[PDB]
Amino acid sequence: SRGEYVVAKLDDLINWARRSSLWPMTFGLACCAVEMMHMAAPRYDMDRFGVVFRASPRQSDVMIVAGTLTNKMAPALRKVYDQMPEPRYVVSMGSCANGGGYYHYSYSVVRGCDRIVPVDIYVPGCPPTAEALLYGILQLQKKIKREKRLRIWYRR
Amino acid sequence: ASKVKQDMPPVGGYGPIDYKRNLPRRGLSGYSMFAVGIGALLFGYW
Amino acid sequence: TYKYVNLREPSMDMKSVTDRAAQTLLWTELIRGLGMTLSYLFREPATINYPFEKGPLSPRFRGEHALRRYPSGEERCIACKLCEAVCPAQAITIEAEPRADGSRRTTRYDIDMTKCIYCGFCQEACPVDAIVEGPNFEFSTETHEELLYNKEKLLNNGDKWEAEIAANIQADYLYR
Amino acid sequence: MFMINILMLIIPILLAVAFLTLVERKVLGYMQLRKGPNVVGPYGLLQPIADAIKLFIKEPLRPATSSASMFILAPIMALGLALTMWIPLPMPYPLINMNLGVLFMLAMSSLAVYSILWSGWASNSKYALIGALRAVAQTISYEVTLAIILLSVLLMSGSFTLSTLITTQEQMWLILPAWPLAMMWFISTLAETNRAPFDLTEGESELGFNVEYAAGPFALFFMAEYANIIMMNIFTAILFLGTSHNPHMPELYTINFTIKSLLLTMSFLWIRASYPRFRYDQLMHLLWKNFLPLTLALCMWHVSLPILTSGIPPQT
Ligand SMILES: CCCCCCCCCCCCCCCCCC(=O)OC[C@H](COP(=O)([O-])OCC[N+](C)(C)C)OC(=O)CCCCCCCCCCCCCCCCC
Ligand SMILES: CCCCCCCCCCCCCCCCCC(=O)OC[C@H](COP(=O)(O)OCCN)OC(=O)CCCCCCCCCCCCCCCCC
Ligand SMILES: CCCCCCCCCCCCCCCCCC(=O)OC[C@H](COP(=O)(O)OCCN)OC(=O)CCCCCCCCCCCCCCCCC
Ligand code: SF4
Ligand code: SF4
Ligand code: SF4
């Protein structure tokens, strides 16, 4: 068999394992954390997708920033991100985290969490519905499904 | 002529709604619970 | 009026005292708690099968802003800027000038969907039902720049969701 | 053929631990009015496999440990001992037919505390050490009652042989003559394996000792911990729910004995979903002030009861 065929299928096996076992670390900072709890509640039950309710920072694959990131909180956020073992993804939930939202023009609010850490998915709303955050999580799964780490290493 | 129509309770009002604590009583008394427990031990030893 | 929650005097007769001894030694009220969790094990779970099933919503739901047209195809917006004045987040930016035919029409209409608090004041202020919040709530992006809507993105949304937007407004405009 | 026998014991243990994670997540879900894993494979049957691959291709941390050799010794010892506690179990025929099997399981079980203590040192964190000390003090405290309760039961059996417990219960389960001991044995097994309502380690808002571990090394601690949950519930069924053994149809024993061992393992998941968590000072008082006085008193009763009824079991 060809080398380009084994790498293509190995890429699908690692992608399948990674997107089927996303363990999130939730930074519940503000009202957006309430909607994140309703995604774990029986109506939607994130756990049935493989997404565990709560995970410790060192056992986690995705960081969900749900609430307003203040200037007194930003260094703590970056520290937790740097200690996440890779691969690691960040989901930005709500207007506050995306761009500052209602407090954009405040002196004590970071205008968007994407200028502190890299962001993979933006979930809009104030707050996003629990069915809108779930749609974002399933959109991160498909993004991980398109990764081609092994198919790019083989062509180096 | 069209009458006013807005959300209203039904004529005569809604049925009663329970709100009080209703933890019921179940099981036997302490005397009988101890009697059954000791009885089991005696049969086991025999 | 008021009531006491925890002001009971436990009886000290032998039968009552023995009842609490059986409870302490035989763990009666702990096993009463195991039974309740056992009952839920045999109840039908409340989970829905997303994305094949969706959570119920109502005609008043506030989702993705959008710009509507008249049945002739002419834009409803006439650049009055009431929505820009009322927006508590200052998420709307507008510029206008006379159109080639002389109409009062916008040349810029941007909504920053990361400043927006999805409050609905823009559609309450509009005198011509031009800016509305539609029923779409699944429009998450992969970059920050895709959430800065301009007039072209908002007009595309209106043409895209007009069939559902019109029916919702038909169902609720009598309460407004 | 013996080497084939060892592999026929090890691999099924790991597979059972792998699918116990799924069953735990689904029983907890239905007791919470939800479902649990049902997307990764039919009814979530591929969820365990996805989790395993994900952990073993995730980059590990390995911080600046004070030793870096205890950090690798701790998970080897935990998993190595966890598999070793299965070799004398009669199901119904032991892999290793020890004469003092019951004493062998106490001895190996008391060595599992080192992996908790060593991982505390290796983390190099002062706070992580405090969490390790509380976990160690919990484990040693509750294995005082495991040893005395076991001695009390064996006074009705006559030996430390694990297969003699099958003969002892050939007319009646030992749960009947010794239900008070069974209660305190069952709770003592939860405390040993750091299970709710005794999971202060995993009980965030007060502390765990295995916090610096990620990826494969973390899974090794996890696998050992869950293999001990199955093993202790297999021990309980043999001890208090003896299954009749027919030498011509040994499979009949294994089916009945497995069903009991599963029902007792599901009881662990049932108890996790029902109760809040003990405070550290409160589970210590549950042992030094409630269980130990009763265990000592019942030990006196069980040394004398066989003598005063003329019911001393045979030595052999
Ligand atoms: C004829 C001679 C007869 C001799 C023998 C006579 C025996 C008579 C009966 C003696 C009492 C029986 C002992 C019962 C054990 C009492 C232990 C105790 O300390 O109780 C108080 C203790 C604590 O008592 P306390 O906290 O309420 O207070 C103690 C005293 N003060 C008030 C001063 C502090 O109770 C507990 O153990 C707490 C339980 C923790 C949660 C456990 C979850 C239970 C889940 C259900 C499991 C069901 C058992 C499954 C068994 C399956 C086995 C296969
Ligand atoms: C305040 C009261 C406190 C409680 C006091 C004690 C309660 C009474 C004793 C029960 C507690 C001890 C447990 C004894 C287990 C005996 C089991 C049993 O009951 O079986 C009866 C059995 C029947 O005879 P069996 O041999 O089976 O017939 C067939 C012969 N082919 O025959 C036998 O099993 C053998 C006979 C055993 C007798 C042992 C007990 C004798 C003790 C003296 C009796 C007075 C009680 C003590 C008084 C002082 C208390 C401080
Ligand atoms: C005990 C643990 C030790 C063993 C470790 C696990 C190894 C054994 C696992 C056996 C089950 C997997 C079967 C073997 C791997 C084959 C998987 C496969 O190739 O699926 C391909 C198919 C998608 O392929 P395709 O459509 O061509 O690609 C499109 C990409 N967009 O994928 C699909 O979507 C098809 C839908 C079915 C895919 C799942 C397979 C059926 C599930 C069987 C569950 C029962 C087995 C698990 C329980 C026992 C534990 C092994
Ligand atoms: S985006 Fe809205 S709901 Fe979320 S934290 Fe900010 S104000 Fe609260
Ligand atoms: S919903 Fe409210 S915050 Fe958002 S654009 Fe409309 S008026 Fe502004
Ligand atoms: S309120 Fe309506 S008509 Fe006025 S500028 Fe806004 S969208 Fe246009």
Image: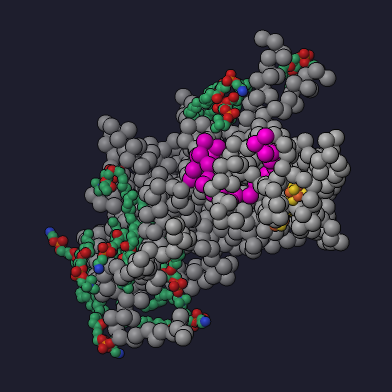
Res D72 quadrant in image: top right
Q: Name the side, left or right, on which D43 lies relative to A78.
A: left
Q: Name the side, left or right, on which D185 lies relative to D210.
A: left
Res C64 quadrant in image: top right
| Image quarter of the C terminus of chain C | bottom right
* Residue D37, x across and y down, in percent: 52, 40
Q: Residue at x 64, y 63 (%)?
A: D206
Q: Pick the residue in front: A27 or D243.
A: A27
* Residue D222, x across and y down, in percent: 59, 45
Magenta: main secondary structure: loop
Q: Pick the residue in front: B28 or B38.
A: B28
Q: Pick the residue in front: D31 or C95.
A: C95
Res D187 quadrant in image: bottom left
Q: Is residue C157 above or below residue A40?
A: above
Q: Is residue D313 above or below residue D292?
A: above
Magenta stretch bounds: C47-72
Q: Residue at x 55, y 53 (%)?
A: C174
Q: Is residue A134 above or below residue A12?
A: below
Answer whether residue D146 is magenta in the image: no
Answer whether residue C68 is magenta in the image: yes
Q: Pick the residue in front: C146 or C79.
A: C79
* Residue B43, x across and y down, in percent: 22, 61
Q: Residue at x 69, y 39 (%)?
A: C69
* Residue A114, x across and y down, in percent: 81, 46
Q: Name the side, left or right, on which A40 lies relative to B46.
A: right
Numbered circles on residues, count: 0
